[PDB]
Amino acid sequence: VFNATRFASVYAWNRKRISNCVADYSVLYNSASFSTFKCYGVSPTKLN
Amino acid sequence: KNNKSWMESEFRVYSSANNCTFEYVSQPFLMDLEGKQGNFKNLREFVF
């Protein structure tokens, strides 16, 4: 999703359903490849 | 009966599918579709 070919519009957003899998989120927080990283209600290290 | 090849034609499982939450597909294999007559030779028991 982050490295997708092209993103959708603000009113017809491409909602990707994610289920039955795992993923590292601390690497995304420390990826140094994002402009905005704002998590509300939960820390990026807590949700891991 | 004849010129058989035991090939699949009809797939009448369902009409449509939407709002999927789980998906899984096993590795490719070749099922023994050879239709034989007589007594029962295999017993596949399952519990759900």
Image (tube, coloured by chain):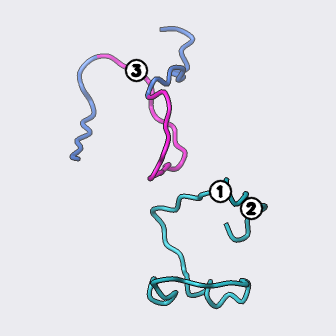
Chain colours: A cyan, B blue
Disc 2: which residue: A7
Residue B34 in the magenta stretch? The answer is yes
Chain under label 3? B
In space, the residues marked 2 and 1 are separated at their CA atoms by 7 Å
Residue B21 in the magenta stretch? The answer is yes
The outermost residue toward the top is: B2
State the predominant SS element of the stretch in magenta: loop
In space, the residues marked 3 and 1 are separated at their CA atoms by 46 Å
What span is in magenta?
B14-37
Q: Mark on residue B35?
A: 3
In space, the residues marked 3 and 2 are separated at their CA atoms by 51 Å
Residue B22's place in the image compared with B32, above or below, is below
- Please indicate whether residue B26 sits to the left or right of residue A32 in the image: left
- Observer-side mark, 3 or 1, equals 1
- Residue A20, quarter of the rendered image: bottom left
- Give the crowd class for mark 2: few <14, some 14-19, many >=20 residues within 10 Å: few
Disc 1: which residue: A14
Q: Residue at the spot x=47%, y=61% of the render?
A: A19
Q: Earlier in the sequence, mark 2 or mark 1?
A: 2
Q: Amino acid at mark 3?
A: Gly
Chain under label 2? A
Q: Residue at the spot x=78%, y=61% of the render?
A: A6
Is label 2 in contact with label 1 (beta carbons under 8 Å)?
yes
Q: Residue at the spot x=45%, y=31% of the render?
A: B32
